[PDB]
Structure formats: structure tokens, C-alpha cells
Image (cartoon, rainbow, N blue to C red; front, side, top):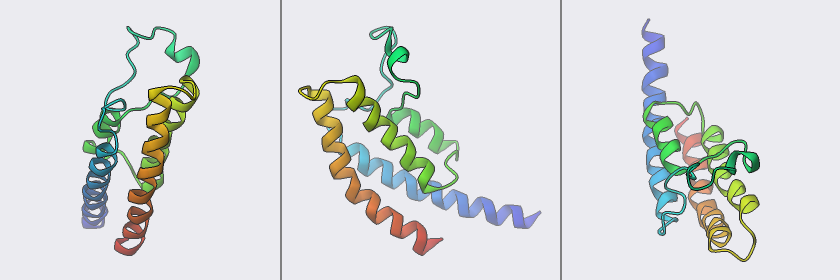
Length: 121
């Protein structure tokens, strides 16, 4: 069907728009602490602490496989990154300080991105 075609083209263009948003968010991690999944070799107990790990490259696999049906699903994954960090790592750490920084700065990118999803449909 063609009504299936227009659902796709509208997804394809969410997927376009999220790509931009992720690039902006991942510029807020200049140190690349969030670039990649926490290594299980390096931190073998990690999953005893964090049940749903998340990182930018894992979000990016799922984005290029059109796997975010809306913005909320993308926003949930981003918050996973931040929240996991701020539980696993103590307050007086480079790691926790960087999640606090990404959360504050990424809140601006997301607050505009929410309007452009609603506007553009």
C-alpha cells in the first residue's frame, strides 16, 4: 500500500531530525565519556549496578535502523545515559560532573527539538 509509504517518509524525516539532535547532544560530550557503552571487560560488575546501560553509539545504531518511533523514546534513551552515570559514579567525580553538564546543556537542544516535532508533525 501507498498509505504505508507515507508513514515511512514521515518516519524517515523524524529519523532525519533526530540525527541532527543527537549530533548536537554528542557535541555536549567533548570528552567522549558517553560515546561508547561502559566496557564489561573493564567493569565486570556493571550490570549488577545498572540494568539498562545506554551510550551515544548504541542510540546511533538504533537511529540508523529507524528504531525511534517518537521523540519521547529518544529522550528516554538520553536520560538513561545521564541517570546511570549519576548513580554509578559518586558526586565528586569527573564522570558525574560530566552527566550534570550534558543534562543542563542538552535540555536546550531538546526543548527546541520538542517544538519542531510538534510543528512539523
